[PDB]
Image (cartoon, rainbow over all chains, first blue to last red; front, side):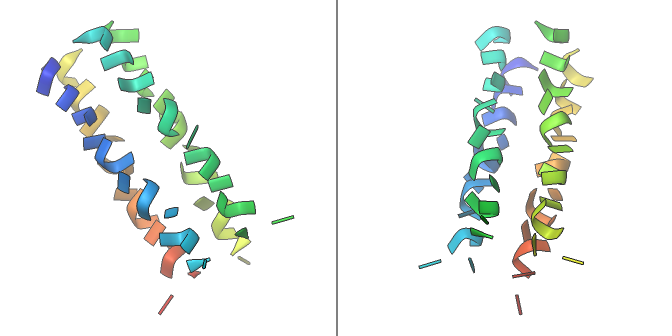
Length: 32
Length: 32
Length: 32
Length: 32
């Protein structure tokens, strides 16, 4: 149930870091 | 619980703006 | 509540089309 | 309800593989 959905949403937290970091992978291929 | 999941989904709202804006970062590296 | 979370997850459906289509924006900047 | 939300979140699992694989599409356009 409810708490163990909340603790899936706080995984989908991890995937929305890994969104950020692996876009910021691409920006720094495109970079400094 | 339920309402404070809904108010996580409306964070995952924020990450799916930041999807958009930081793709639209890349499109404008690739741009005008 | 429950049904109106389900009908947020089936928005986050829409954002995970717009993931796809606006990556496939970038692939076709990078293209045919 | 609850279990069939959990089994939507474990689809949004599939979309956050397809995030990964179709970014890693772009990295290997940009590549080896």
